[PDB]
Amino acid sequence: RCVCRRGVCRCVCRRGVC
C-alpha cells in the first residue's frame, strides 16, 4: 500500500506492513 499523489508516492505502512 503506497499512496501516490500526482507522482509523489509515499508508503503509508502499517508499522512495517507496507
Image (cartoon, helix red, strand yellow):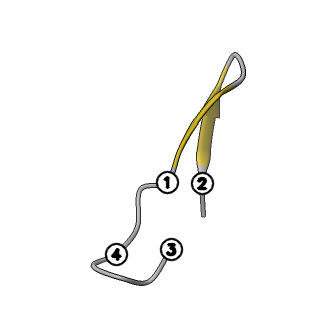
Name the image quarter holding residue 12: bottom left
Label 2: which secondary element = loop
Label 4: which secondary element = loop
Residue at 44%, 83% in the rendered image: 17
How crowded pointer 1 is (Cα within 10 Å; few <14, some 14-19, many 20+) is rated as: few
Q: Is residue 17 above or below residue 6?
A: below
Label 1: which secondary element = loop
Look at label 4 and name its amino acid: Arg
Name the residue that disc number 3 marks.
Answer: 18
Q: Mark 3 or mark 1: which comes first in sequence?
A: 1
Gap between marks 4 and 2, in whole Å? 11 Å
Look at label 1 and name its amino acid: Cys
Q: How many marks?
A: 4
Q: In this view, does 14 lie above or below 17?
A: above
Residue at 60%, 64% in the rendered image: 1
Gap between marks 2 and 3, in whole Å? 7 Å
Name the residue that disc number 1 marks.
Answer: 11
Q: Mark 4 or mark 2: which comes first in sequence?
A: 2
Name the residue that disc number 2 marks.
Answer: 2
